[PDB]
Image 1 (tube, rainbow, N blue to C red):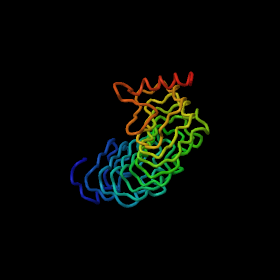
Image 2 (cartoon, rainbow, N blue to C red):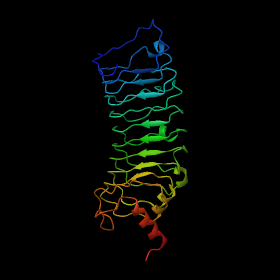
Image 3 (cartoon, rainbow, N blue to C red):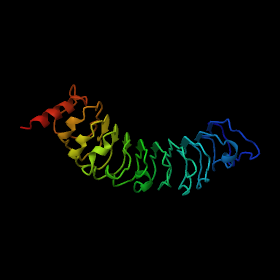
Length: 266
């Protein structure tokens, strides 16, 4: 039930048990608060979707037992209670986009996918840097300043890291690079980056690197020639060291030229 005009106060009857329900789509309707009696009616619920609504206040404790896909994007919500996800030990793909959010209250250790773009995050919360099983993270279009290095992440299964439309001064990677050897995507567009550290050559599994739209980079390092898996590499609106975009320069032979330059630089 996902495009109707379901008015606020969508309280469920506490006298009915529906353990068969698995997916409960309540998105886009009108909701101002999360349904009150979820934990006593739809006990075996798996996916709860509430995007596009107008949920405002701090959410209910939500002690439902078997969440796997939670979606609270496109709301008008300021902050979450400190015990929001404490009693949902199987959450995997929490996502909260287009929300006036600031901090993350103790995500469960079973989290895998986490999308948090279009939120007013002054700095990346510490609760994300100690998730033991995180796989992808998307915090684009936020006003964060410092990106922590790969020795502060406590997770060996990073695969995507999207941070476009930010203002990150540095791309600190010389600390311990090999921990991010699993990373497949890395988007640093629209940031204030001036130079790429040479240690980016260690991330041998990179598949989609984006550092375009910086207006201050003006250079690439020679170590990037070891990033054989790259197939796309945007160079939109920034002046490089050579004239390009005549008939080729399709982001695959440029890395070949970079590797050859790394072989001998005369």
